[PDB]
Amino acid sequence: VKISNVRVRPLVLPLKQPYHWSYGIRESFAVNLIEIEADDGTVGIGECTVAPDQTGTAAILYRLAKHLVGHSPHDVAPLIARIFHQEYLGHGANIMRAANQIFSGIDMAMWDLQGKLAGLPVHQLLGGAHRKAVGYFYFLQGETAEELARDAAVGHAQGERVFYLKVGRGEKLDLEITAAVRGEIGDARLRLDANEGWSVHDAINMCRKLEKYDIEFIEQPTVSWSIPAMAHVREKVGIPIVADQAAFTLYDVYEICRQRAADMICIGPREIGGIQPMMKAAAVAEAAGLKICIHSSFTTGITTCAEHHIGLAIPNLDDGNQIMWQLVQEDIVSSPDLTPKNGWLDAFRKPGLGFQLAEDLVAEGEGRYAAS
Amino acid sequence: VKISNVRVRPLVLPLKQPYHWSYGIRESFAVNLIEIEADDGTVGIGECTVAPDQTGTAAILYRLAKHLVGHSPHDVAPLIARIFHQEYLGHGANIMRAANQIFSGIDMAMWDLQGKLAGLPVHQLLGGAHRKAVGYFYFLQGETAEELARDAAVGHAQGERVFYLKVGRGEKLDLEITAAVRGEIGDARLRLDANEGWSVHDAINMCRKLEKYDIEFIEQPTVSWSIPAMAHVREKVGIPIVADQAAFTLYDVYEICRQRAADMICIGPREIGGIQPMMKAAAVAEAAGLKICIHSSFTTGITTCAEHHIGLAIPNLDDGNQIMWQLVQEDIVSSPDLTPKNGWLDAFRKPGLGFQLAEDLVAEGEGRYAASREG
Amino acid sequence: VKISNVRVRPLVLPLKQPYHWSYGIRESFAVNLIEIEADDGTVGIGECTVAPDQTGTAAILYRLAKHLVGHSPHDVAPLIARIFHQEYLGHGANIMRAANQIFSGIDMAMWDLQGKLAGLPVHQLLGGAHRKAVGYFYFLQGETAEELARDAAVGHAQGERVFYLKVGRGEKLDLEITAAVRGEIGDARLRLDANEGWSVHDAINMCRKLEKYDIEFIEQPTVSWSIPAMAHVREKVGIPIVADQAAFTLYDVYEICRQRAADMICIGPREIGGIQPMMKAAAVAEAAGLKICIHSSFTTGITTCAEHHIGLAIPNLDDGNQIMWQLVQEDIVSSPDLTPKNGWLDAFRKPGLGFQLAEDLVAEGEGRYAAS
Amino acid sequence: VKISNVRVRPLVLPLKQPYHWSYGIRESFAVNLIEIEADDGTVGIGECTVAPDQTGTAAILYRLAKHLVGHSPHDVAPLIARIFHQEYLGHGANIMRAANQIFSGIDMAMWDLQGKLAGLPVHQLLGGAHRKAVGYFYFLQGETAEELARDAAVGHAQGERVFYLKVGRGEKLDLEITAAVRGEIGDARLRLDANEGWSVHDAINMCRKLEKYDIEFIEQPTVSWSIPAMAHVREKVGIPIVADQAAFTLYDVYEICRQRAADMICIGPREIGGIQPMMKAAAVAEAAGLKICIHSSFTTGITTCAEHHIGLAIPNLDDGNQIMWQLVQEDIVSSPDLTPKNGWLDAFRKPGLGFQLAEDLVAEGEGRYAAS
């Protein structure tokens, strides 16, 4: 079997509700699908994030994927390495993180394809599942303490086990929203995401003031480019510190480990470059006595399935992994049901990444892209 | 004064001779020019490298540059910081190196604009020139020992001072071309570029075998992603080791310094994100007792001028800086003359980056780009 | 355009109230102004501190400045480097901190001149402002708890945001003044300056006893000559530690960073040698994941303006920077108004450093010097 | 007995021949004598270097010295500490090196006075002499290989044991002169002063190329401000590396020791602040298993005597210490004879620093100062 075709389909998908970010409001997510068809008709599907420009990154994704035509889906590793050396390194552009953003979709598509051709779910191509179900967090939403508390109340009543709250919104508001959320979730586990928002001394003082709320850990308190700075804060504060944006590549993971810069590493396919690279990141972390928590992205149910299979295949995995498809108004995955039950998703067993796409919703997504 | 327009012009320019690399030969270089126009008619010019796709990166360069319209050329630093946070970080794309590739041309053009508005060369906007001339290396060309030695012979007779030779072509050939070049340049300085080609133990053995040829230093012997691996090699071998591809961002530079991973750092605008960022990298190196050698790229005379002014402004600078405009068949810079004499280029003094573009050659470059898009 | 003349004007300026220091009370500040005139008539102005002897340092400043005559104001960096090498290093006087003290004023005047010639404020010659306003602290004054509590009440009344209190006056008094000040500022931020006054074990114990008062950070608890001693205390105490006197040169900054000896670095032009060197120090701090807080000096509004533009041009800056012109009875800067509003000074935009001097007040200052 | 008066005498003394430096030729140099007189008529005499301005530094020396009036010559240590805190630290001028430059002459005079009062040589006030004589180097002079070769031949003929040659004049010339010198001194010891002139990689390559000439050590190859850079070079080269300009204060010495940055430390009274400070620096080196080599300065026989007693009193001392009085046309010390014999100067036994000044030469020196 040989890869016969590759297609890139840019999509724009509306969110259920406005997503507040650094620069205004966000009402839709955008992804670039990558479809890899084998000569026997079987198709592997994956997707990439699109920053800084969907049209530009789509062109890049297409250019890299065309190199796969005529080759074997079972040679994904050496193929990506060659394409990387040829289109990036040979030109002096040693931008591994940026390359990873693109190869992530390519890699998940190839394994989806391999799984479909073998009639096996991806995790059974990676050594087997280390758990019967992957555990996920509860991504709280809201701009005010009242809204966040209401959301936490409902989630708690629904059986959610790991609450995820973003902070770094200023000292006063941070303590108010953290107090409000804790007030509605009893003794349940609460994790805070500082999103690189604190300087070293502010991180230390905020951790001190947040301890009283029983925080499981604080994710990426400091500017991600400095692993030493993160280590500096970790060694001083009493609340565990988890690396997120500080960890993109296999090498970043290694640096974090040897410098004992974090208590756990949160990384996903988008940062490391796919499914297989995640297993390698997981191995390094395991060797250093640390666990992996899956970091997600503003994508669709496709990434959800990939991250799910990645999770099942990793022995040293957290039980409060990230998940984001629920933010989409109409997700493009028609099956399986990606809705966690009590913060768990029992192992998916269909071939490849195990999903079916809602072609009608995908078409609408392409239409919105063309519209813009 | 405020920025009124921005323009991106993708170009394809032929090379004097084919450039050999890991994947066949290369017949031309591609760059994306970025023009930034102020409401008074003044125009700043810069350029960006294009990998992995010129059309895609040109689209990204344009999108970022449009954010500048309506703002001051004198606010380049905070403007870039904001654009980076908005189009990249806010979306979870913490790809500093990739972002730097694009911002390099923007920053390049911004300082050119500032210099033209003030009527001063860029280096005098950065504190003044620390030298009367920037020193450059001699990039040897050839695939065989014979061609390389002959080129070395000529360069030496012409007064070239710092020879640059690419190695990592296998032990036998590496030692053969090195010996051959050494044999034609008397006792002149010789630098070798391993181009990330050696594993740790091979790097150690190659250095041992190359020592007899009096090597000033070997550049990036190991895979660029691992700084510890480079430090590992440096501490073991007798020939000094220079960081190249391992050093892209301000943080990479700091890591190399704190780990004493290299004896000198070779970095340029394309990697760090511009002229101003280079000043920052230079300061970190200076604080660590290290010097900066400007790393160039497959670009044009526009970058040569930017790198030239960057060089004059850096106090802790090498005198064997990289230069590449000479590889282009017909470079797009009509003035000044970028040809070094005895490996030197006396300080350029015209406003901004100091160049004049050959409009017709740029147009032809635009024409080639259009052609490459017929497919 | 070239520099045609240079002149040094030693001044002695009375203070609003007595200043208490380790050896009594200071009734006035003294500065040595440095004016650099271009052949077109434009004049750049800066100032230097004068210890250990105003006459002696006035003599040095003039000798160094005279080397500028005949050269371009745009070649400030290589000029200072050459002067430093010829007048200091060539004689075996590797006294970088001492030379920085003098070059601070020179560099200050050179950029003022450059800005005036270009019609642009100094921060726009340095890349642009990274904020609309620079944030400043409230320099508390008083020798007893009652006095400090009163001054604190005044500051809180006018909306100050960051209170600065000097400690190291003995355990009993330190706790009593910190308690009284905290009692007048509600939940406002409080910073303590130990002024190199504690031994390693006393610093550890005092930090422990001061924690209850919610301290943002303690500045330079240990003797400034030992970077290791400072890191030693930082790693042990719960309150963040800020380096001040330990950081004078670019290399000192790198050492503190390299050794993670401080949580933030407080440094000013007087210590590092000017405006441009501060940019370099800030870059080193930035690469290490640390921020800069501007350390001021017993000087005039001239330095305030210089420190203001430096602050605007630094991306990684604190918002409780030091300011000292308000201590002078009649500051020599006639414009602009250097009085912060709620701890802020909106960006100055006039050419160069942006100030105009009250020649009458300067002439008076020269008179007091001549009198002494 | 208390100090009754202090006087500062600026001198300018011609050299035997032009001294070549970075900025041309130096045909003479200056010193600021400091005489401390006790109420019983006894007078202690010391001297200070004058960079960056003799008049300015003379004024500084006078201001600091007046503080000694009315106090005991036996309280030199606590007196200098107070003056330092009062005139420097209390004003935020933590310029220890600059202060040491001045205090060096003061301490020098105080121990000379203490010696004369007790009728004992200074080394016998410091614990006793650890050797019968102090070993000194042969300061080679010349600008070309031929001149250096002839001077070396002269030195060898008269029994010199330790040759000191300045390099860093470019690879070709450095190699030429070193070969030239080696060919005239047989197997004698040869030391090379790189004088902060090499970058890290140049230092490494030059040491390799100079190795064939049998070099005892290379002094300060890299910029003095970076101790890490010096350790970096030391760890790579085969020739021992000696710290010089990198070591000025007690703290610099400790840092060099702590970091194993040098194989020996070359430091003198001008850098550390006097005679007694040298004893402390020597103790730190000793505790670290390192030896001290006396670094001299462009001074007169007075400093030679001060450094001589310092040498006798240090147990962990080198035998190729620096000496510079021989460069002066008419040294101001009329006795003892400071001319080394086979590179040795037997222990001086006269009271204090044990010298007598040629009144007439000093007066003429005061004349030249006035004339300049």
Image (cartoon, coloured by chain):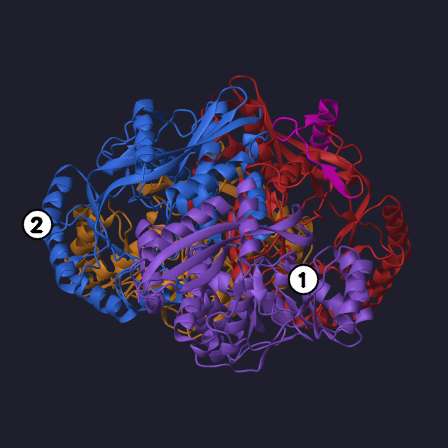
Chain colours: A purple, B blue, C red, D orange
Q: Which is more toward the observer, A3 or B81?
A: A3
Q: Is residue D180 left or right of residue C175?
A: left
Position of residue A287 relative to residue C314, above or below, is below
| Quadrant showing the C terminus of chain C | top right
Q: Is residue A191 left or right of residue B332?
A: right
Residue at image position (76%, 60%) is A174
Q: Where is residue A156 shown, x and y percent of the image? A: 77, 72
Which amino acid lies under the numbered mark 1 shown in the image of this protein?
Ala
Check the image and name the residue furthest to the top: C40
Magenta segment: C343-372
Q: Which mark is residue D157?
A: none
Same chain for labels 2 and 1? Say yes or no.
Answer: no
Q: Residues within 10 Å of mark 1 (few under 14, many from 20)?
A: many
Residue A350 showing in the rendered view: yes
Which amino acid lies under the numbered mark 2 shown in the image of this protein?
Glu
Residue at image position (22%, 64%) is B207
Q: Residues within 10 Å of mark 2 (few under 14, many from 20)?
A: some
Q: Where is residue C88 shown, x and y percent of the image? A: 46, 44
Q: Which mark is residue A203?
A: 1
Q: Is residue B228 left or right of residue C137?
A: left
Residue bearing the label numbered 2: B146
Q: CA distance from mark 2 to mark 1?
A: 61 Å
Residue D259 showing in the rendered view: no
Q: Where is residue B363 shown, x and y percent of the image? A: 33, 26
Q: Which is more toward the observer, A169 or C254?
A: A169
- Chain at tag 1: A
